[PDB]
Amino acid sequence: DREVLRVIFPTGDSKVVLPCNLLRMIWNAQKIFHINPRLPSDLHPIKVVEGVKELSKKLVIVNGDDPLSRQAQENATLLFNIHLRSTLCSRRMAEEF
Amino acid sequence: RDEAHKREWNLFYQKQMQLRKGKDPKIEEFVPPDENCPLKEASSRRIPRLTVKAREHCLRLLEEALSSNRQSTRTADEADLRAKAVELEHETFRNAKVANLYKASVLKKVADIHRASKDG
Amino acid sequence: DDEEETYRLWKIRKTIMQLCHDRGYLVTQDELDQTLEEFKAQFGDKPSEGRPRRTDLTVLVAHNDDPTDQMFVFFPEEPKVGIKTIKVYCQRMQEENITRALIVVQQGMTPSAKQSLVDMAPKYILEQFLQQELLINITEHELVPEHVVMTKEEVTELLARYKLRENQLPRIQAGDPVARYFGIKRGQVVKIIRPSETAGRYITYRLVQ
Amino acid sequence: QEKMATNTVYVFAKKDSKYAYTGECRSCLENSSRPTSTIWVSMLARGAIGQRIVATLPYIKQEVPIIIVFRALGFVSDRDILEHIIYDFEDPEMMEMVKPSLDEAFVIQEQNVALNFIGSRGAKPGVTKEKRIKYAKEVLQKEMLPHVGVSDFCETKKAYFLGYMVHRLLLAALGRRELDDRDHYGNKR
Amino acid sequence: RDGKLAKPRQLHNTLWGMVCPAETPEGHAVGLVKNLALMAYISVGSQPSPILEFLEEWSMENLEEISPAAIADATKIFVNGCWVGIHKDPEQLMNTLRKLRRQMDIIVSEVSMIRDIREREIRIYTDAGRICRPLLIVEKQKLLLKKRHIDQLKEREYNNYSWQDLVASGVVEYIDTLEEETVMLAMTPDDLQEKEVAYCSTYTHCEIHPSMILGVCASIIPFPDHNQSPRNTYQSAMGKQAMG
Amino acid sequence: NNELEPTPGNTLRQTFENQVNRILNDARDKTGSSAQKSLSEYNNFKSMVVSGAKGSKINISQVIAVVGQQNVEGKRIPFGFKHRTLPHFIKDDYGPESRGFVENSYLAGLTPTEFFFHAMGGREGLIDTAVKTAETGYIQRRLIKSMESVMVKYDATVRNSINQVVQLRYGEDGLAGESVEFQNLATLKPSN
Amino acid sequence: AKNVTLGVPRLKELINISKKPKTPSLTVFLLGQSARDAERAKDILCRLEHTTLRKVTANTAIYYDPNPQSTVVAEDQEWVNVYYEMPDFDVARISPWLLRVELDRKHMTDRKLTMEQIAEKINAGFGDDLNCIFNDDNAEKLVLRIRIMNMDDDVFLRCIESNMLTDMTLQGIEQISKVYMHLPQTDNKKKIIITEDGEFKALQEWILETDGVSLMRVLSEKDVDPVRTTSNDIVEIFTVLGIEAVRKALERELYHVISFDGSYVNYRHLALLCDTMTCRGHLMAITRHGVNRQDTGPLMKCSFEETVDVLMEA
Amino acid sequence: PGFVGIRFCQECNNMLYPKEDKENRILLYACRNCDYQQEADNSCIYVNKITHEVDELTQIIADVSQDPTLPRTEDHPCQKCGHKEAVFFQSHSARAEDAMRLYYVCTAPHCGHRWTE
DNA sequence: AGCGGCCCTTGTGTTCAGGAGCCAGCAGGGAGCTGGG
RNA sequence: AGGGAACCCACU
DNA sequence: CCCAGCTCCCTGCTGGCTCCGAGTGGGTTCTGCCGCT
Ligand SMILES: [Zn+2]
Ligand SMILES: [Zn+2]
């Protein structure tokens, strides 16, 4: 995804326009559930990766199981999926959020 | 627009040249160089309207320039004088493609050699 | 005037090789990655003197799908290409059982010659290129996105998937620089992949008209 | 109501046109139902050989070379016309600038021929040369520069003022005088 | 109003004193409809016959009598756009004409006389529609207006000393734009005072008051020089809509 | 004294004008910054500027510091008269006052020539408004009539009245514009 | 430096698909050493900007010279007799009318031109029928003597001069009137690369800004980047690169116009406008001509413009 | 060399054009509508000053010393008569890009000397 | 009583929103082909 | 049951 | 076996047509008449 992004944005501008404010959603989740950053968390990182995969499968812009619809769906949400994967990392979920 | 006016000039110029040009081009047959010609590629006709005798004269001027350079710097060998002059003439012919430009280049080389001799 | 012409010929040959490779013809890697020194070695270095001669640059390539399909790329010497040279090229193609050819002219081509090219389309598909156009590869410009030619099966799949009619797709002119580069005629559909700041990637289809 | 001042020579430049520089004078008599007669003296933009000065007169639908106009007024010799146009004979730049106009007008060497030429350009040229000359003379007497004079025997004053207009055009073309401003008050009444 | 060019609608430099800079409609007719300044006067016109008679009586040489060789070093003289002759001493001719106009012996106050020094033309205008304004005369860095003139003006109700007496005693002068191009105005008499580095020191006229450049509607604004100019234009537009 | 040499891409007059404009703009900026520094926390100009309710720092500078330079068509006040901006100056005066530099604040008040030059400056903007209105209005109508019938269809494509495909997905991603937000990609800039 | 049209005028130039923009320009990026050092950048600039003979000439003068052996100028006579050593030519085929052209040393050194190149261009444009002779550069003045080899010859030489000054090109491309050269101060024009450490870096490199548009010739030039070199004229982009290239370039120009003031408009609106303008394979101008040529319908068209004409055709 | 003037015929006062005597090969100035000829001396028949290096002092007239709107300086005395005051102005003429140069004219009524520094 | 007929004053006569982009028609130029020598 | 055309001024 | 017209296409200019922001509030003047059929 990093290589794909560097190809898409040849310059060094990382400001993009995307639907969901993932950082603010994580902040809201931290405030709602009283997350203590100073204690170990009970979130299995494999849980994080599996959840991200299922979520990515749940966000469809071009529906259809044929190869054309599959490729169009992958293209439509490519940038948002890259953002989601790089934000909902197992490592970031463990040591940052 | 500009190109149209340009070709306007072109048609005027060509008809004026024809008015100033003879009906038949009186082609003066190229003079074959004498076997004693020290000019490389003396039989070439690459440069139009250039005579072998003109090349011989240019090589003679190069010879005089080299002689002046030698007497100023006291060059030892003499055969080198002739070889260098012939090489210079052949190089000038190879580079230039028009008689007037050829003559100008030869004169420029002569001036360069003269200045070098003056420097010592 | 002598090295400049050799450089121009090398650039034209490199662009033609890239075009042929992009069209699906079998071109070796050395031909694509040929330097100016290699061009001066294989060919001449005094184009005005006649070495190399434009007749010496003629290149024949063969399609990967079937070796029978071959394409010429002729380099006429005359600045303006008339009917007689087109007739000579057509005679050579008929003798050699070739169907496609590319003509890279220097200054241009007569209107009658263009009409002749158009007339015999169903028999001999031969195209026309200005060497000023082939001095660079337009497909490498940052503005030009990735163009691909869709096979009839792929176009049928596309129309079935989107329930479209060919006249409902966006259009690309047959005289478009990229259309000429890929040699796509009317009725063919071209797929265009381009980056997108909103979606990441985007594929759009254009019908050649 | 604002209008542009009359009887004053204005030189404006319009490079998006056929004329590089264009003089202008809205000559109007002291009192007359006839509106102001506008005369132009314009220098052709480069692009034959030199730059030719033409004169656009009222009731003539084709621009005529200035030297033809000066000959129609009764000044045939080049010396007299240049005396009326170029006041300093030791300034060769103006002479070089005016040479093309003299070259343009060489076949027409007499007043009657010039009048016939001017009449031929008229709106309604007559098949008879006499009536064409009559029309041209009438136009020059009454329509060209009314403010200078409308009666007869005013040819010298007309020639002097037209030469002054040509001189102003030449000065503007040579860069010796700034072009007039259309928004400048004082050029307005 | 259809034309969208901004040049005719712009406030030209020459409108100074003649036309109000502020008052103008802000709609489609912005800059095309203007208003006179307070002291601006538009001339009504007069016959050039007395001026031509004086010039002929003067050293001026007719256009017909002269020879073309004499025009190179001579000064062309125009009267209402008619080249009437040439002269040899433009400076003293202009001095005489200015003296006559100030005395009003033969030239009325409305006549505007412009000498183009770089060129060699003297243009005399007696036409109508020439907007002008009155300016004080300065001779040698001193106003011609004195304390006695003000003393007489203070009693105009009794001694019948009006503005026409100022204009007739050569203390004030009507200047139009063409002639205003050739004058050297002092905004205030302070500019005539000696300075460590004199700016001009050759002033020819002085402003009666710089605030006379405004019109009827922009003349009621208090402290209009402390406001942004569009505000002054808007008030000029709104002073006509006030109820009184 | 012919001791000034033109800069690349410019002529001598352009270079001189650039130097003068640079000097005067720097002076205006410095005086404006000094004006900002002088203000107290109780100042109401600063109160309305800091909150963003109304006004800017340029307004404060003009009210307290110099008003600045008045330009007509992007250049200093032109020589409307013969080599003079007004009949109160000498011929060929390129100084700050002559060409329309206002050194007085609005509180101090403008001098007559400054008042006239500022009036010219304001007239420029008034005309600009009066003309831009119609030009932009025609442009807007033309755009609307060009694109009025394009809409999102039930197959999610964007098509015009003729039912021809304009976009296969709206915005190439098929999302409405009112719900997207600015965000930052965290994997683009970082080094390996 | 160079005036660039922006705002509503540029927007009108864009959506109208004007063929004659007020200020067309190119943005030429250089490839190799030309990008780093300014000398080779200046070389390329001179190779681009048009240069007619009138831009380097000091003054021309048409003399009458009966015998070239003895000319009317002492220095010219000396140099000519140095040149005229033999009857290497045909004496009969010579005209006595000389055209002496004095060039400008400053301009020639600025363009790195020489008498040899000018003589070459004169010969190419006029052929061998003329005769041009030039002195050495080390001389005090740059002088060229032109004659016609054998309507009068006088006016003929005058016309030859009046043409040579203007139409003849010594360097550059015809339609490029001026070419500025500068180092960009903003990362939008700087060369962005990804270092060996995988981090973005912005190299500063010389770029050229032309005043005309000859995009094809400029792109084909050596030492000119053909990947990043672009134009602000969209008709030229369409003619040279194509419909997708002009789509992207039109979007770029619209974004520049809109965001020059710092304002933001969502990308999808610009994308939709550009798609509508380029969906049919040609530049559909946002005008009566562009819009009413579509296959929309007479009632659709009549509401826009040309009501009665549209309905009469229908 | 400089710009070439124009000569007028002695019998008709019309412009004389350059021509060549074929047999003698000498430049003549011959009238076109008459049969008059004159001997040319300069031998230069045309001049074009592309640089336009015109000495603008030739375009200045001492009359400008009477202009009240021109600035006057006492630090640039005139060399001819030693007067201390002079009016200074600029080129203000087209065909001069480097037109910030100052030209001085003596204020003395009779001197009228024009110079440049 | 109502139709002829319109006055544009120069029947010959100044600008009836004027200028900017598209489209259409005319004349010129040249490529190529074909009937005579 | 009832109008219109033209022009001018002005407001946002 | 070339020469010189003639046909057919393409170029360039020149001439003509259409368009020129959205609403709103006031006001005044004018929408025939004159000769003799
Ligand atoms: Zn004679
Ligand atoms: Zn003196």
Image (spheres, coloured by chain):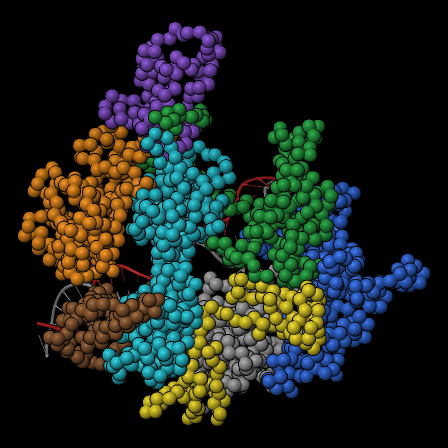
Chain colours: A purple, B brown, C orange, E blue, F green, G cyan, H yellow, K red
Please give left or right for residue K10 compared with residue H33 in the image: left
| Residue F53 visible in image | no
* The C terminus of chain H lies in quadrant: bottom right
- Front residue of A96 and G263: A96
Q: Residue furthest left?
A: C95
**Image location of residue K26, percent across then percent down:** 67, 44
Tag count: 0
**Image location of residue C171, percent across then percent down:** 28, 41
Please give left or right for residue G160 compared with residue E48 in the image: left
Q: Residue at x 46, y 64 (%)?
A: D17
**Image location of residue E159, percent across then percent down:** 93, 63
Tell which quarter ligand 1 is in. bottom left
Occupied quadrant, residue H76: bottom right
In the displayed structure, would residue G40 be above or below residue F175? below
Occupied quadrant, residue B28: bottom left
Q: Residue at x 39, y 6 (%)?
A: A42
- Front residue of D103 and D132: D103
Occupied quadrant, residue E243: top right
